[PDB]
Image (tube, rainbow, N blue to C red):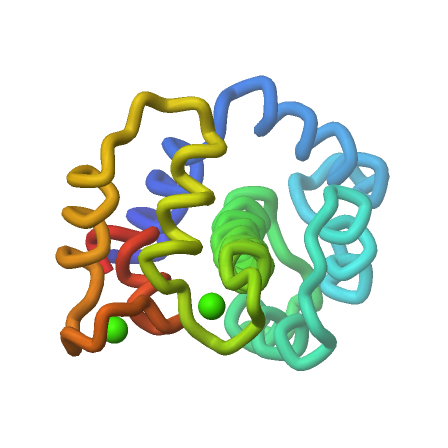
Length: 162
Ligand SMILES: [Ca+2]
Ligand SMILES: [Ca+2]
């Protein structure tokens, strides 16, 4: 992926109204109307738009985009950086939520989901699940054949591909 390839993929990931919303905030720091902002303002615009880069991440980005020393980042490069951050933050949110889901499923807090806990959570959804359906999910998710689902197997069960 060239930079332009990365920029075309960044644009394809976002709806056009979202792109124009991001440009409306970006434009408030341009002033000069040139299609770019100081790299000193990148963190501010990113956080205004709901992203949370660390300082180390921002330094890494600035160094990626400011090799000519102009001290600016353009809008197309800004979109590439926003999509990278959106993907990273969403990944972190999903892992955090899966760890909370496991702590709820594991009613007895022993570090495993057993067939009784699994049957009880699935029946409470209201779905017409049978004991055979519950046993089939258990057997398919239980990689090491100990009769239970630990957090590593839970992550694989839920994420599915993984
Ligand atoms: Ca348990
Ligand atoms: Ca197991």
